[PDB]
Image (spheres, helix red, strand yellow):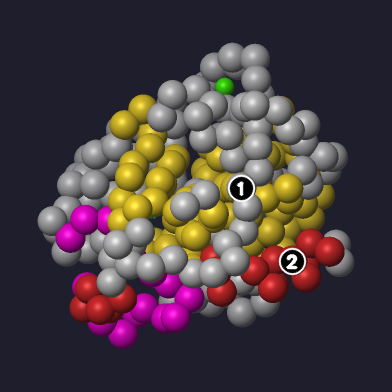
Amino acid sequence: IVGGYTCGANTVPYQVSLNSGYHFCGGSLINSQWVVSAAHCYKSGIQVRLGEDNINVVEGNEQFISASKSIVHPSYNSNTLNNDIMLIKLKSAASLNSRVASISLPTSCASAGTQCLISGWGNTKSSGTSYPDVLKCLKAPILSDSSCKSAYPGQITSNMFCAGYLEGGKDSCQGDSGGPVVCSGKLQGIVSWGSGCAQKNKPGVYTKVCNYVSWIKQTIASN
Ligand SMILES: Cc1c(F)c(Oc2cccc(C(=N)N)c2)[nH+]c(Oc2cccc(C(=N)N)c2)c1F
Ligand SMILES: [Ca+2]
Ligand SMILES: [K+]
């Protein structure tokens, strides 16, 4: 997250850290047994870390759980990033409390201008590298579809949306991938890709979750 703020410990309860000996991606808990993340975050041997603030300090509210199964969307295109969404089944149910909560799925898609909250442990520098240990937050609006496609000609599919600031200086970044985008208390996006970070006229691109609800619901119910 570039140009954001410190969330505060466990203020974003549904936020998950994906670990393979180190933090590599963000994720969202949608129920006690499932996490949603980005397909580009796929790896063999993931451990799901819940209740996390400082990713490098054991503070007492963490639940570290191994993944039993990973399902990448049947149409994920690694070259275009079209359908960048994956489901992760937890080895055992997480314990829901005030520090670990699930985020609901949307019943409808969000409008441009809707304000959202993006969160992650990703890079905090526009151009340079600095990784935080604590969860960073950022309020950002969904951008109209025309601005999104003007910024990335021929690369935006109907499964993507832009959120951020055209003027640059505030964006999600690498390390944030798979991370949630919550608007009006529903999971509307997953951190997918971008062109650099917080650059002028190159906003963040997100998987539009609203298009995957029937796929999520059907997949979980059967696995
Ligand atoms: C090396 C690299 C990427 F390739 C990338 O995006 C991709 C990767 C693969 C395919 C495509 C594609 N258009 N076909 C785009 N995003 C990056 O930073 C990030 C990562 C996450 C968010 C942001 C962001 N600025 N919001 C930047 C990044 F550092
Ligand atoms: Ca910790
Ligand atoms: K990334």
Numbered mark located on residue 221 in the image: none
Ligand 1 location (quadrant): bottom left
In this view, 2 is above or below 99: below
Query: Along the line of sight, which residue is nearer the eye, 30 or 131?
Result: 30
Answer left or right for 123 relative to 18: left
Q: Quadrant of residue 210?
A: bottom right
Residue 58, image quadrant: top right
Q: Position of residue 121 (x, y in %)?
A: 44, 36
Looking at the image, which is closer to me, 174 or 207? 207
46 inside magenta stretch: no
* Residue 186 pos. (x, y %): 54, 54
Q: Give the range drawn in magenta.
A: 151-166
Identify whether 143 is placed above or below 145. Answer: above
Q: Is 47 positioned to the left or the right of 137 in the image?
A: right
- Furthest-bottom residue in view? 154
Q: What residue type is labelled 1?
A: Ile
Disc 1 packing (10 Å; few <14; some 14–19; many ≥20): some
Which residue is depicted at the point 63% across and 52% down?
104
CB contact under 8 Å: marks 1 and 2: no
Element at badge 2? helix
29 vs 9: above or below: below
User: Which secondary structure is most common in the magenta stretch?
Assistant: loop
Residue on which disc 2 sits: 217
Identify the image quadrant of the C terminus.
bottom right
**Residue type, mark 2 in image:** Lys
Crowd class of label 2 (few under 14; some 14 to 19; many from 20; radius 10 Å): few
Q: Which residue is drawn at 21% across and 56% down?
A: 165
- Residue occupied by mark 1: 103
Task: Determine if residue 196 is in view.
Answer: no
- The first of marks 1 and 2 along the sequence is 1
Residue 5 position within the rendered picture, expressed as x and y whole percent measured from the top left: 31, 31
Q: Where is residue 130 in the image (x, y as percent from the top left)?
A: 30, 33
